[PDB]
Amino acid sequence: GQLYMGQQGPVQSSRTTFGVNPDRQANARPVYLAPAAPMENT
Amino acid sequence: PVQSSRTTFGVNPDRQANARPVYLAPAAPMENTYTYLGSIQFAAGRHIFGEPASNVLPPQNIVPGVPTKHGEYVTTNTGDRLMASSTTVTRDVSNGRTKVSIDIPYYDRNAVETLKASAIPGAVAPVGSFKVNVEVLGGGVLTGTDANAQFALDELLSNMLMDAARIAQDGPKNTARLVAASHGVMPQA
Amino acid sequence: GGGVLTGTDANAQFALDELLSNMLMDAARIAQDGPKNTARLVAASHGVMPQA
Amino acid sequence: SSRTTFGVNPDRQANARPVYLAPAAPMENTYTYLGSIQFAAGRHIFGEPASNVLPPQNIVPGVPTKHGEYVTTNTGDRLMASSTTVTRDVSNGRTKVSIDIPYYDRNAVETLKASAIPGAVAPVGSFKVNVEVLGGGVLTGTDANAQFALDELLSNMLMDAARIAQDGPKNTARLVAASHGVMPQA
Amino acid sequence: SSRTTFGVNPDRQANARPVYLAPAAPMENTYTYLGSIQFAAGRHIFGEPASNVLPPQNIVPGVPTKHGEYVTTNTGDRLMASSTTVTRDVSNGRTKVSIDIPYYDRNAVETLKASAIPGAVAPVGSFKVNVEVLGGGVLTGTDANAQFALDELLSNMLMDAARIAQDGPKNTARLVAASHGVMPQA
Amino acid sequence: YTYLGSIQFAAGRHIFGEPASNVLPPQNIVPGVPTKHGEYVTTNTGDRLMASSTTVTRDVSNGRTKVSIDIPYYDRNAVETLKASAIPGAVAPVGSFKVNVEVL
Amino acid sequence: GGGVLTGTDANAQFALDELLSNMLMDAARIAQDGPKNTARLVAASHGVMPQA
Amino acid sequence: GQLYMGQQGPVQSSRTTFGVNPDRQANARPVYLAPAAPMENT
């Protein structure tokens, strides 16, 4: 890619996937279910 | 052939065409969500979020006075060792159905904080996003309905919107209600 | 609200809950935002944002 | 066709029985001990987990799976986030749990700390522990209640096997870098 | 040749460490439970061991071995003596303990008893449980004391793995004749 | 099963097995797991009988719930000839009786 | 109730009659078994037996 | 099949259909038909 100045000398900029953990947690979470639905506004 | 039927008085109605142009906001306010993000200091779990440019999102592709069936407001998110990333509010108005969607990205807090603590100059791209959709099916207005009446229908759908959002977020903040949802359980009560 | 990250603490999932609910509120406000003098929801054909 | 049998009847029951799958994996023993030694033994440095109990990664409630994983993230000073994994396989009456935890080079980590220089380090290797239960081959006569009894029988053999594996004085070498086994005299 | 290293040094310590070998194998948990159910579940009937602690069969004190076996004899009414075996393998930093106990056809056994006829019966099958510790790959810096610490770390992971394997209500199926795993809701 | 105890597990040349429990445990029903089909089963044993399972099946789907009960029976002539002759053979079931119940 | 065996006595067919009727009673009891606090028959989608 | 010990010596277990009469009686039995149907419970 593009070129910039690092302390070693002119150095090429680089884009890597190193060090990014995209692992996800399974959707296994019980959620609250309301005992009634309030439609007061409408 | 003699056939049986179930009768009520009336006639199948005459529906009005969906030819009514509607108002389009000149900017999208996101004050509630961004004040809360300031509250949690833009971090939760190993999701880290970006600071916006504005709490109110300007339009990106909406010329004024130009009819548009699809439009986007967008503001840029910046942060320490974060690659700038856009948060987006999308509005689709067509055929009597209006739909607003909000998409905000998040980054890997583990990567960001490892970079910060190690004083590494890398910038991190977003790992994912969270989205919220809202939809109003306002087609099929009856022919008799005039303009003033349609105003009333506007506010009626507005209040149904408010009720739907309240019913969605309803519940104690002590218990799980939205993210990583698997199934719903009504309390013993 | 799917796809939370692996290190998301059980406690932090509540914070994420509230974040999503605030996005909900903002979305409904953006949906109905506008003067009540002018058409905004039903029989919608297209959007027209005003010049001034 | 119905047949009278003389002698042993070896008819086995088909391995078609759903089994309970824990909603999370507790790793309390190992992580409390890791806290005990301050996450460092010799040149091995370990990361701090996000939780002592690991949530499911690819398991959904109510959906049968034959392979499932619980996972958390170890973070650390001058360390790159590395996941700790607990894998469970259930198939054909054989159920197997494996645990994998990674480690890092303490010399690199403390050399960076002491040099005050921007580097960070990735894992160097891992330690793994497997546990396996061969529960296939249940005979025809066995009903559900009896199968529960067999469940507990196997779990007790599991406990015996783990104790026999870790058995021995802590004065003396017993697991890592093992070459061969030797029994003492008297 | 001596070299200065930048970054991670992955040199591993050769797996050339003798490990303690128990003079006998305690199987107390499984045999007490077998006494609890009177050595019979469903159509599976088990034999009574000679001892709860199994003596070595092919292990001699002071002689290094990479494979060793403890064994006792199950005897029973109308049953042919059948050995119960506990096998331990130590090689290349990997140590593995396996337990094998045989069972018999209860229908044949009780049909003989009830018929008062001379027959006796041999085993029909067995149940097996394996436990495995992959302790190879110790880094260069690790000294003996640190290796003891790693010994205990692995043993704690062993305990965690056995608990995660047997985890669950005894109301419900969890090991034998397993088809797949299912997680409950809420 | 109380009635089977009444007739002493025999009628005609049908002979039945004694159950393990009057109440049948579940065989393939994990708790908290939605199941559209499930089975309770207990084992039947008897003198010179090959152990055989009696089964209660429940199917819940699309608003229709259906319970079926299946109990097996053996050839009393074979069983009693073996008993009287002191032969150690065990007999497999010759047939079964079934009762279905259904709610739409 | 088909397929009775050949040596089934005329008298024993009555005993079989009563056996089947008792299976009937057990089947209906298993069909409606459950607390009346909770849903059990109509609009049924699936079964969920409780943990405790 | 499997092997066991009989008084003759070690003997192979065997499973045979010998001595099992599965003949069935025809469904030719008139049954009682109630003169009315009581729906009292419902």
Image (cartoon, coloured by chain):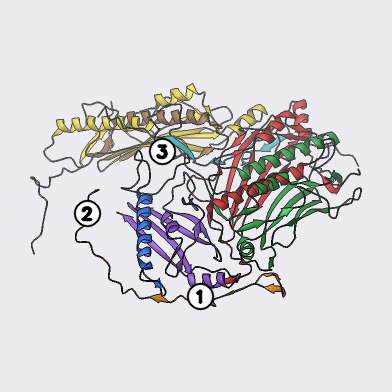
Chain colours: A cyan, B yellow, C brown, D red, E green, F purple, G blue, H orange
Which element carries disc 3, helix, strand or loop?
strand
Q: Which residue is mark 3?
A: B184
Q: CA distance from mark 1 to mark 2?
A: 43 Å
Image quadrant containing the C terminus of chain D: top right
Chain ID of residue with mark 3: B
* For the residues bearing labels 2 and 3, Cβ distance under 8 angstroms: no
Q: Could you tell me if residue D66 is visible in this image?
A: no
Q: Which subunit holds the residue at mark 2?
A: H
Nearer to us of marks 2 and 3 is 2
Q: Residue H1: where, in percent of width, then height? A: 65, 72
Tell me residue B114's x, y (percent): 64, 31
Using the image as rendered, state which of residue D71 and residue E149 is in the foreground.
E149
Look at mark 1 in the image and give the residue it sits on.
H20
Query: Looking at numbered disc 3 in the image, what kind of residue is underneath it?
Result: Gly
Q: Is residue B163 left or right of residue D139?
A: left
Q: CA distance from mark 3 to mark 1?
A: 56 Å
Front position in the image: E10 or B77: E10
Q: Which of the chains bears the disc numbered 1?
A: H
Q: Name the residue nearer the viewer: B182 or D91.
A: D91
Horizontal placement of D45 versus B109: left or right? Answer: right
Taking the image as shown, residue C18 lies to the left or right of residue B148, namely right
Whether discs 3 and 1 lie on one chain: the answer is no
